[PDB]
Length: 108
Length: 111
Length: 8
Image (cartoon, rainbow over all chains, first blue to last red; front, side, top):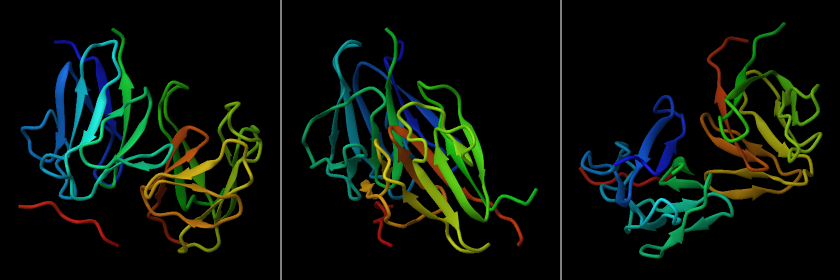
């Protein structure tokens, strides 16, 4: 399967940027090295959030999985309540705990 | 030529690759004008958009928005920075100028 | 290990 999106974890205290590919289906974000998008940092929940992608040409849906430190949309600033679906927009900035990320749609 | 006390990273994006800028003691103006300390030559950036002021060698920089059209936002916690309000910058923290994410890093230098 | 809470 070719990736259809990217999650960019920006550079920070943890070192240079890390880029994670996003595929059709369930892409789990969490600390567990099993996760599709493994962010191995103590403040990230073991199962933190899920990005669900139904097709290359459909917006991903992000949901927080009841994480301890939350998932936020950076701009406009919002807290995502557990279990509520949010459609991701290309270039949208997301916080998983204190880790800023950016979602990019790929082509095609 | 003095030694930069910090730096501002403009992340790569649809606009092009990453750019990095020195921040010095004193006033550092962020804007689209090409003679700004931090020149972000994008039309959505105001001519004088924001300023990062470093009052003294070992003091956290203060970021202020200069009444920019498209705004400055603090990323964590996520909130608009109203014009004139001083925000103390923390190492590795991200800031949005308009829609462009940028990161501040403190450099490990003597006076 | 459980998740580390973020505080100040």
